[PDB]
Amino acid sequence: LLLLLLLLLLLLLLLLLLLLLLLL
Amino acid sequence: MSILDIAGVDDTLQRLLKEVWFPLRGGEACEKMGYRYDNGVLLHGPSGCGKTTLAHAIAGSIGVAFIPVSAPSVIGGTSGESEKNIRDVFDEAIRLAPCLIFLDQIDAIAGRRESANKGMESRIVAEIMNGMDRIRQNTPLGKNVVVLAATNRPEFLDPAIRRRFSVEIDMGMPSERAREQILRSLTRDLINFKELAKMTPGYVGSDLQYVVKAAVSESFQAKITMEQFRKAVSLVQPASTIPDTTWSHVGALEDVRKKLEMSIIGPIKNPELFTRVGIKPAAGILLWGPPGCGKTLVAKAVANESKANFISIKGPELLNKYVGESERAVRQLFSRAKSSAPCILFFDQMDALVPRRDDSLSDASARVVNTLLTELDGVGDRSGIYVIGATNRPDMIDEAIRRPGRLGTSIYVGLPSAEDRVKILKTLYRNTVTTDADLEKVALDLSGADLGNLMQAAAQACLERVITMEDWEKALNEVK
Amino acid sequence: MSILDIAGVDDTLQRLLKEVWFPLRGGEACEKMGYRYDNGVLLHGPSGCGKTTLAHAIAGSIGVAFIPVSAPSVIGGTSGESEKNIRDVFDEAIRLAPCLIFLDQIDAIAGRRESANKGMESRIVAEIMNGMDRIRQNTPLGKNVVVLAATNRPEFLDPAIRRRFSVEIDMGMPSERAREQILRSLTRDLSLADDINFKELAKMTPGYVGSDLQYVVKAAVSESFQANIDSLLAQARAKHPVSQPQRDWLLLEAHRDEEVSWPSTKITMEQFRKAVSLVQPASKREGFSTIPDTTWSHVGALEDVRKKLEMSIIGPIKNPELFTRVGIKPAAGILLWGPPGCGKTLVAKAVANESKANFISIKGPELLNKYVGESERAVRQLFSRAKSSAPCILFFDQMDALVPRRDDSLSDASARVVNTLLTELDGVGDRSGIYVIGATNRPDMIDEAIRRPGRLGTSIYVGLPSAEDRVKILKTLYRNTVTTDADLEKVALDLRCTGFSGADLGNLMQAAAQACLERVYTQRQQEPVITMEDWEKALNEVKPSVKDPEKYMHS
Amino acid sequence: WSHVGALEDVRKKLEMSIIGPIKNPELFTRVGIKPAAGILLWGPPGCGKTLVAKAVANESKANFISIKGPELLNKYVGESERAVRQLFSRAKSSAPCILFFDQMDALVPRRDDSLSDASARVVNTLLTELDGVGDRSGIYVIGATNRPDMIDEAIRRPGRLGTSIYVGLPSAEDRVKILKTLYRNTVTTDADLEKVALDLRCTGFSGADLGNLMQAAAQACLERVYTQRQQKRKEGIEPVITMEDWEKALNEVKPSVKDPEKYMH
Ligand SMILES: Nc1ncnc2c1ncn2[C@@H]1O[C@H](COP(=O)(O)OP(=O)(O)OP(=O)(O)O)[C@@H](O)[C@H]1O
Ligand SMILES: Nc1ncnc2c1ncn2[C@@H]1O[C@H](COP(=O)(O)OP(=O)(O)OP(=O)(O)O)[C@@H](O)[C@H]1O
Ligand SMILES: Nc1ncnc2c1ncn2[C@@H]1O[C@H](COP(=O)(O)OP(=O)(O)OP(=O)(O)O)[C@@H](O)[C@H]1O
Ligand SMILES: Nc1ncnc2c1ncn2[C@@H]1O[C@H](COP(=O)(O)OP(=O)(O)OP(=O)(O)O)[C@@H](O)[C@H]1O
Ligand SMILES: Nc1ncnc2c1ncn2[C@@H]1O[C@H](COP(=O)(O)OP(=O)(O)O)[C@@H](O)[C@H]1O
Ligand SMILES: [Mg+2]
Ligand SMILES: [Mg+2]
Ligand SMILES: [Mg+2]
Ligand SMILES: [Mg+2]
């Protein structure tokens, strides 16, 4: 049998930083 | 499955007659005029509202090739697998025209490609767009293909995908008539359903199915009797709560009760009687009185008699420190009350929530007031939402809050002076089973919530030492 | 599909005659001058604007070899399979020159290889770049290859691929003249009644795209076939002596296999107007409010306010040409202010209903968000929806909480929201067709830059009704829920109603109706209609709600 | 410039600072003028700051990027400063380019302790882009604001925004030029326009008030047409703004800049 190179997916799921706002 | 298995959607069942039945079954007329009637229908609403069952019931009532597809069933592991699964679904329908494609949970695969940066997910959306265009272009005149889809959050769909559905149907929360029809549709093959319908506000079609199963299950522990449903209703909760506090739980407060029997309780039990005389209910009632007089208890009694849900807010609990979060919490209370109609919104300590918009009130304290002003405009009238204020400082609230059509009418909850104390204590003791003369001198000793705490605190001394009159004098020197 | 199947785009068909037709059907001219006229055209615009139908209409019109390619169809499983499918497309076009390649939804496979970081995705982009270079160098100088691509997101394309399209054609939302042409092409093989006026249909579909107008024709066709369905249900009911809709499904199910013929009908102009209301355009699926049921019959008096709103908003919306001749911009900004309960929201929900335009209502500080730039982005997105669905009415209820005056102590989270609205109302970008209504009790708390001509230049005062004004309001309130008319004047003119707003009169009527129920119950335990004695009961237990009118009259 | 009436002083400053060096940079290079300008237009609202910055963007015939206040702000940590850096990359690559910041006080607030940390990074990003290590030659920056004192003092220095041009309320003579400009670009003669613009009822009117005055005159024309059309159609026209219509507008329109000295400082 021949072994083949296949393209697949990934999960990744990076986490991003955020900026907030405050009251007086 | 059959048509009878789905009920309370009379509007939906008649709209889909000209949109699903006609393009499929009545395809002979389209060929005469040469018009490709390839239609796309999207069903959206709260979870457990019969979206899945409606598609299957209509599938068998037409008699065409039905292709039931779920979105997770097409996602693959390799690159071209996921797109070819969707491509095969639309290619099969063209060969099987007329056909009825049903893409259940379509929001799983048809999400917005803006946020979705994944390559496969973007190509999934583009594959559905190409598929629906082939149906519109590569079918015979006499054979049309109708695409059905269901999603709990239609806004999550891509706008390019969503525009391809000409018809959107909002199968929302069932009403009292709808829930009455739903009960008659599940128990037909086995009773005053009006009482059952009105005692279950906010229930969905799936929740009413558990109640039917609970009554059937409870009928086999020993034909189903009416009293079994009442027990079964309390067993299954919807996926807020009607209070269990009756007016028997409330001592005195007759003048206060009379006003509420015409302002709130009145136009709920008999909506038509108050409709004929033109009594349009306002947003609600402002209860003002000293703390500890059972203002929260009175509101719970009103909801219990009216058989409406109860939501309570403690006041400064909503005040967030972020910009739009203090106002969003208020706007979220009225969003849940709309889905729980009829419901009663109770604002305890509302003086610190909506003060007067003076010339010096900063800005954060003024956005919350303007949030309630625009939210009380969708309260009452023909919505089922009722708002009850509660404050010991009624003159510290903004004038616009207390105008007619808003919480304008003011009701004073009186402090127990001489005989109210006696009535309250007897009511409290009736739920913890001495005579009644002994219960008088305890309450006649020289507020309203103090007596409730006094009774249970006096019960602690009984446990340390059956409740006797001689155990109350010792507790009168340590309860304030 | 054909050229007739695409309509409403005359500039696009004019450009494409020398950029797609000439390179393909003018091969001899290019060879004479020895110039390789290989072109690349990128169509883009809102979804449903006839990008795919335009490509296939041109493909069948030109009559050259056509290679329609859908972007997801290229992707394969193994490593080199995906790139070889692209390589096969461009090599086939070179072999079939002159040829026209249509890459539909190219943004699916031509995304930015910077952000879309993978191994196949980068090689797919590099293969299209290599492919689009072979066509303009391997063709034998006499036959040209034109690449057509369509995408809803031209900004998602990789700049190396976007730059290879010499022509970008933007197909925006159709205008009134274009919408009429689209309807005529859609209603071309159908049978119509001579009463149908396409000008009326075009003017009643403000924010409709070519796909939306198709649904109107689709809904109108089913409307004309309803008479052959109700008559067919009557035939089914003749054999069988559960609700009404469920009976229809079961009766048709019980027949199903029965074959009947539908007589041919003609779509009526009345049916078209019904179809337009049924069809919700894709631009109004999200962000738009429902048209209020309030009408001018619900508003008593306020003739001065009604005249200003009719001239400033209702007028130009219904007669844009009349107001354009005198030179009035199709955009108005109105600020309604006064003491609470005097009818600001009511008179603003009647303009939104009696103008037949689109309506968006903002509930105070509804657009504010805790994240940086999200509060301002909602405002910018708000005016994008209101512009694509023009004419549109933006109603800012309790607006003083959204645009406070930029003092030296207004912080910066709320000062940036004001500056966003300053540019949206009157900046560089056009906002014609957007009419803004603001209602507030504290107009002095609104920034002065907001209250200037071009943003909210017109201020209308809605104050406490006069003695003769309360007569009109009380009659209006009473007639909408059903005493006579002579007693209503007596009740309204009573001095115990001094200072009563329009909300107090509604409270007076509610209080008078409650006294009727008390009277009925007494006359029952020993047909409820409000009597004159009931009114006098409410004339003592009802006090005005605006205790200090001077607090709002001076602003 | 045909849409801009009066403002001759402002027009001359903008031609020497932006339009001049763009069209013939060879002449300005010999005297030693860098191919980059920073202009801050400020004054009371409605007096023509955005209008005059759209004529410069059009008369200079250069590339144009317009920023609508705090349009570049993003919720993520680095994405708002990255937008500013990307803004000057496109402008530099397509020089000459005109960057217009409308209502700029919301993008460069004065840096204080009470200022948000996230909004202080955007200010410092613009400080380096306008005048830092890298060169911005061929980039001309125009800022328009009502509150020049709320802009960071480092931004308002030569090399970033060197010159401040005050666009204030028109004078009595200037209101004649503005009213004629507004009228002739939207179609009474010119003798009546001088009387209307010089009327004492037009005291304190800005450019937006004169445009509002003309709109109120057109609405008075339509009311006159409406009433007369019914009378001459039931019992028994041309909509043109007459001098009697201007009288109704003068008694209806009030000035909008109620405190001119609040912005004149
Ligand atoms: N209106 C209704 N009439 C009759 N039965 C109903 C109705 N609504 C729900 N049901 C019943 O309750 C259950 C609802 O399940 P269903 O799968 O149909 O819900 P859904 O709307 O698709 O939501 P989800 O996908 O979240 O489950 C079924 O057993 C269905 O028979
Ligand atoms: N100008 C037009 N003339 C005639 N029909 C039109 C026109 N514009 C759109 N349509 C019709 O509306 C639909 C548009 O679908 P089409 O595939 O052409 O949209 P699109 O621009 O490719 O958008 P998408 O990117 O979402 O596929 C078709 O049914 C087409 O017949
Ligand atoms: N002029 C009027 N004609 C008829 N009904 C009126 C009038 N004014 C008030 N009402 C009645 O009283 C109600 C007052 O509510 P409305 O929203 O119009 O007040 P408002 O002017 O917006 O004040 P607020 O600032 O308190 O919201 C109306 O909904 C209507 O029932
Ligand atoms: N000098 C002028 N000549 C001609 N028309 C003018 C002049 N000044 C103002 N206008 C008119 O009034 C409008 C005022 O809008 P403009 O954008 O110029 O105000 P602004 O100075 O930017 O003030 P703001 O700070 O409120 O944005 C112009 O669009 C134009 O119609
Ligand atoms: N009139 C009354 N009748 C019966 N119970 C009362 C009465 N007044 C007060 N109580 C008791 O006092 C308690 C008060 O609780 P709650 O109403 O939540 O607080 P507050 O009275 O401060 O609003 C209740 O649990 C209730 O049992
Ligand atoms: Mg389901
Ligand atoms: Mg398309
Ligand atoms: Mg209002
Ligand atoms: Mg400006």
Image (spheres, coloured by chain):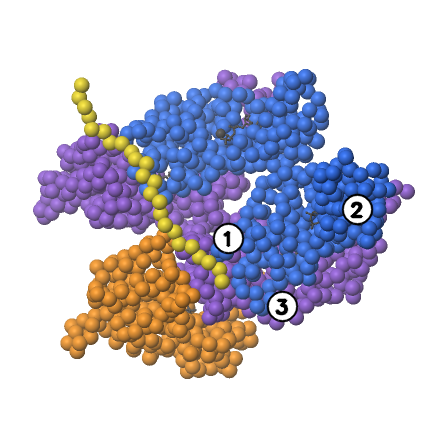
Chain colours: A yellow, B blue, C purple, D orange
Who is closer to the viewer here, B126 or C226? Answer: B126
Q: Which residue is mark 2?
A: B473
Q: Amino acid at mark 2?
A: Glu
Q: Is residue B223 above or below residue B71?
A: above
* Lower position in the chain sequence, tag 1 or tag 2: 1
Mark 1 vs mark 2, foreground winner is: 2
Give the residue at x 85% y 40%.
B436
Q: Is residue D18 above or below residue D74?
A: below
Q: Is residue C167 above or below residue D60?
A: above
> Relative to residue B215, is residue C136 drawn left or right?
left
Numbered tag placed on residue B325 in the rendering: 1
Pointer 3 chain = C
Who is closer to the viewer here, B360 or B177? Answer: B360
Give the residue at x 20% y 75%.
D33
Q: Amino acid at mark 1?
A: Glu
State how far apart marks 3 and 1 are (Cα): 29 Å
Q: Which residue is mark 3?
A: C552
Pointer 2 chain = B
State how far apart marks 3 and 2 are (Cα): 58 Å
State how far apart marks 1 and 2 are (Cα): 50 Å
Q: Amino acid at mark 3?
A: Tyr
Residue D78, by quadrant, is bottom left
- Could you tell me residue C409's position as x and y percent? 48, 68
Label 3 residue SS: helix
Disc 2 under 8 Å from ligand 5? The reply is: no
